[PDB]
Image 1 (cartoon, one colour):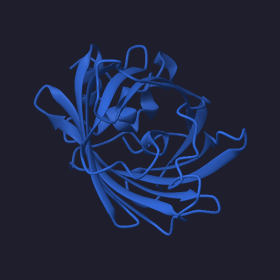
Image 2 (cartoon, rainbow, N blue to C red):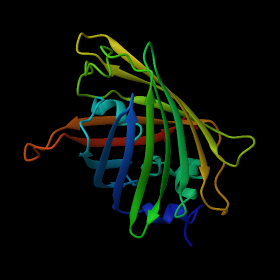
Image 3 (cartoon, one colour):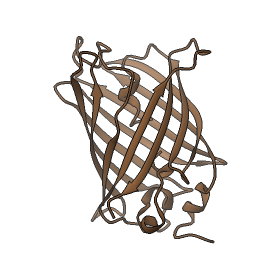
Length: 229
């Protein structure tokens, strides 16, 4: 026992990651699996995501926030404020409502937990009220990603956290599609968890392709560092 939380100790090195997502958007059903690893030491994620079942009815960038904030770098001075690591290995439920301005919405429920050596993110996603010739269903989003601040605060009733931020998705005409995120996280386990002060995560993301993958897919590099304390 060496650190503020027991869960923290699980992230000192490279950790394999699995991601399974079951999705319905305006009826169109689809699944995605992803494999890679994260090193929370540097706040770094490497991940490749594969369309397993269905035709992908939405642009890949719209799924990035849905498809493991426990891999965020918390510097030494902020170690009392890492809720995400503290809840491990049992993990946490992560729930969102995602409002795409002038378009539809995603509701997501995910379990993020260790299954053995592997950190695993299991998600259900329902999207509704998307327009047929809109920026999502019309695949009008650039295949790229912006840097964002993710604002975190303690839930003063639930032993968990409330997270708020706004994603900016580039549209290929040079304009921006906003996606407003309302997020809550709650421990799966009964163990004590860290209830943070107000702070944020500084996020950066690179989207690429494997030139040796014929399936519909997204390669993702991510770096996330906690700040604001």
